[PDB]
Image: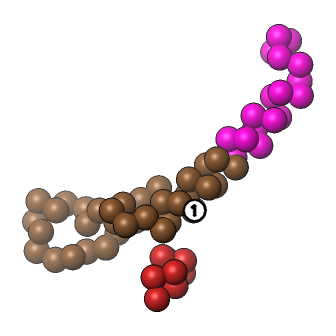
Chain colours: A red, B brown
Amino acid sequence: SAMVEELRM
Amino acid sequence: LNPLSPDIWMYVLLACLGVSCVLFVIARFSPYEWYNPHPCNPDSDVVENNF
């Protein structure tokens, strides 16, 4: 979830 | 620009571009850098970005 959050943003 | 033989020039070119890119990547996965602009009203946990 963290990698997704700060990757897609 | 004579003193440095033209090689070292483009070397540092690629060097700073790489270090800047990795800076952006590191700041991307960085805990404290999300800095809720204007915390002087702490009213909410607003998540913003930097770098």
Query: Is A7 placed left or right of B47 in the picture?
Result: right
Quarter of the rendering containing residue B34: bottom left
Tell me if residue B16 comes above or below residue B32 in the rendering: above
- Pointer 1 indicates a residue of which chain? B
**What kind of secondary structure does the magenta stretch mostly adopt?**
helix
Query: Is B13 placed left or right of B5 in the picture?
Result: left
Position of residue B1 measured from the top left corner of the image (x, y, whole percent):
81, 15
Q: Residue at x 48, y 68 (%)?
A: B29
Tell me if residue B31 comes above or below residue A1 in the rendering: above
Position of residue A1 measured from the top left corner of the image (x, y, whole percent):
46, 88
Q: Residue at x 54, y 77 (%)?
A: A7
Quarter of the rendering containing residue B24: bottom right
Whether residue A5 is visible to the viewer of this picture, yes or no, is no
Q: Which residue in the structure is indicated by mark 1?
A: B25
Quarter of the rendering containing residue B7: top right
Whether residue B44 is visible to the viewer of this picture, yes or no, is yes
Q: Label 1 amino acid? A: Val
Q: Residues within 10 Å of mark 1 (few under 14, many from 20)?
A: few
Tell me if residue B21 comes above or below residue A1 in the rendering: above
Position of residue B37 measured from the top left corner of the image (x, y, whole percent):
25, 62
Residue extending farthest to the top is B3
Is B5 part of what is drawn in magenta?
yes
Q: Which residues are magenta?
A: B1-17
Q: What is the secondary structure assignment of the residue under circle 1?
A: helix
Query: Is A1 placed left or right of B22 in the picture?
Result: left
Is B12 part of what is drawn in magenta?
yes
**Camera-side residue: B11 or B41?**
B11
Query: Is B19 placed left or right of B13 in the picture?
Result: left
Q: Residue at x 56, y 53 (%)?
A: B23
Counting the numbered discs, the total is 1
